[PDB]
Amino acid sequence: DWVPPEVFDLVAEDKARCMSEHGTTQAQIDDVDKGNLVNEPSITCYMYCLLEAFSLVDDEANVDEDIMLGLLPDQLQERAQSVMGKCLPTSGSDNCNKIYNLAKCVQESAPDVWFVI
Ligand SMILES: CC(=O)CCCCC/C=C\C(=O)O
């Protein structure tokens, strides 16, 4: 992708923790990455969990746009601001479901640059 390998090491402890907490499998993550998203807590609560580990969302799955933007390469800033304009604020029944809807929105809007670690 555009995601550099250093980022995988950085997320490794939290990834292991969030998969363990939520019953997530690598296969589920690969599915999401392949654009296939279902409203299963084991995947959706994983995504919320990891986002939270990096202060990208708060206790009610409100996205920190600035942190999100500061994390992305300089190239995607422009298209990411557009995707956020369409897909934020988050909404849903709970934290996991809010990230499910966000994931659905962001994938529908910017498949090219869609991905989850
Ligand atoms: C849903 C998902 O995988 C997003 C993970 C965000 C983690 C990024 C952590 C560190 C960085 O980008 O430097």
Image (cartoon, rainbow, N blue to C red):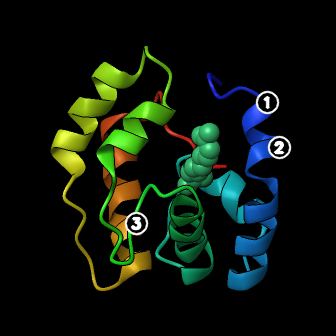
Few, some or many residues within 10 Å of mark 1 (<14, 14–19, 20+): few
In terms of image quadrants, where is residue 5?
top right
Residue at numbered disc 2? 9
Query: Is 71 drawn above or below residue 106 in the view shown?
Result: above
Query: Is 46 drawn above or below residue 113 in the view shown?
Result: below
Towards the viewer: 39 or 63: 63
Query: Is 116 drawn above or below residue 113 in the view shown?
Result: below
Query: Is 86 drawn above or below residue 20 in the view shown?
Result: above
Residue at position x 67%, y 49% from top?
117
Using residue 2 as the reference point, say whether residue 5 is left or right of it. Answer: right
In terms of image quadrants, where is residue 109?
top left
Towards the viewer: 88 or 14: 14
Residue at numbered disc 3? 99
Asked if marks 2 and 3 touch (Cβ < 8 Å), the reply is no
Residue type beneath disc 2: Asp
Ligand 1: does it lie within 8 Å of the C-beta at label 3?
A: yes
Residue at position x 50%, y 35% from top?
71
Using residue 30 as the reference point, say whether residue 91 is left or right of it. Answer: left
Using residue 65 as the reference point, say whether residue 96 is left or right of it. Answer: right
Residue type beneath disc 3: Ile
Q: Is residue 34 visible?
A: no
User: What's the CA distance linking mark 1 and mark 3?
Assistant: 24 Å
Q: Position of residue 116 (x, y in %)?
A: 60, 49
Towards the viewer: 36 or 13: 13
Q: Position of residue 64 (x, y in %)?
A: 33, 52
Asked if marks 1 and 2 touch (Cβ < 8 Å), the reply is yes
Ligand 1: does it lie within 8 Å of the C-beta at label 2?
A: no
In terms of image quadrants, where is residue 86?
top left
Few, some or many residues within 10 Å of mark 2 (<14, 14–19, 20+): few
Towards the viewer: 17 or 31: 17
Residue at numbered disc 1? 5
Using residue 61 as the reference point, say whether residue 41 is left or right of it. Answer: right
